[PDB]
Amino acid sequence: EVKLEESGGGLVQPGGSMKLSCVASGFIFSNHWMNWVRQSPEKGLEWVAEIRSKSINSATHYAESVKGRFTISRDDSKSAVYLQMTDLRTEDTGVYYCSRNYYGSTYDYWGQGTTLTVSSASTKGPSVFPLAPSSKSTSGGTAALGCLVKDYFPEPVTVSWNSGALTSGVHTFPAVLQSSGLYSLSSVVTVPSSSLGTQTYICNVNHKPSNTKVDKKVEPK
Amino acid sequence: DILLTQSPAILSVSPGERVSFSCRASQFVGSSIHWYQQRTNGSPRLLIKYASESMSGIPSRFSGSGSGTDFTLSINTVESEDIADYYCQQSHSWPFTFGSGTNLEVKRTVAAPSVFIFPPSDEQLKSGTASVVCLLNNFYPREAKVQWKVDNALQSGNSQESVTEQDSKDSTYSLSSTLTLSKADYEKHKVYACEVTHQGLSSPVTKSFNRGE
Ligand SMILES: OC[C@@H](O)[C@@H](O)CO
Image (cartoon, rainbow over all chains, first blue to last red; front, top):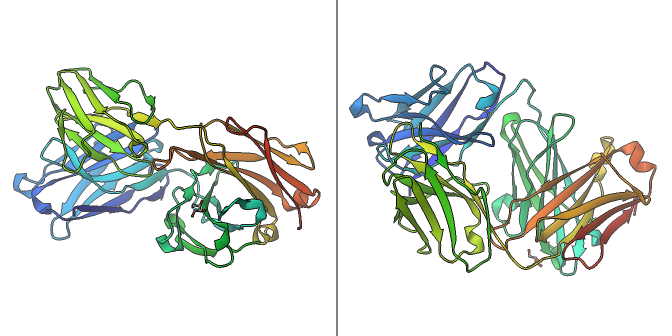
């Protein structure tokens, strides 16, 4: 199994710096070309940088829109590829994917992405409130419950239920930007109404830029 | 640089039908077009390389064709699990470029939403704010109307809605509407109601509660 795992995203002021990392496994790392490809609502999928093998001088190539500001590097002893970003701009905001390109053809493996936000605003961790089940959130044999993840910045937060053991029926809604400048979202799950008060439901909320890791037990009302 | 034009940007098809995605290159790219699938909250997955060679593990209903500047991705019988965005990519010349993507919606029979309402939590109320949430779960088609009434007074400008992307297991959408009030304005009223209209409902559905019950 090939795996690529990015990290290092977060919030940075305009003009600031930030270094992304990616660790690879499942192929002979030092023989292959590692890439960063970013994604944003405005520009879609956009190749950013490539570093090729040590055997051909670890040659680095950059998209014209980041040339001079970004530096890609690799450490073959760690199976790591890095992206040092400087003089960051608002338009650099996006999801940054670590990706392998098969010698100038397909991007045949991708990581899961790490999110970069270039903004003058500050980091704020979320507050987490239960959306408690009751008869008012029961529809026949289905009950709904959830978690309200309120007043955080920047994106993203991840939510899981019962430490990931509960995935069926879960909807985590796209975040909305409130007038305050802070994001807000709800994660809900639908369950059998008979399981209210007999099964435990805990939403696990993670907001890395503020190092919030909160588990919230959601109880019937 | 080579521009890949993917048009149309949205496709909507019924299950069991054949669907075709179009990718046109502004210059000759030979056969060096690659197709990717990106599911909601996921990463692009390689499907076809070099216009028509499907990768190992891709279901056989996927196939590609074309050469020169005109390329097609086909799904000969579409299922809900095929709901995603589809991107093309050229590696004929540097730099490699991607199309803008086409989104695939798979139609289904009309499904009225289940409607649920949640009062604000005691914890949030202690912080001075009351958020009331109305959930419209697993409906189709996407269009739905949500109105907040507080003691039968229609509310305006104090709510926000968020809609999920179409679900690949059952082709439905879900929607949340959050009404936010100060604790002071929350305590000045009693009845908090959520009213939902949708193609699948024979008449509007109202979910409500009395504050403090
Ligand atoms: O999440 C499915 C819900 O409708 C349950 O009643 C079925 O087990």
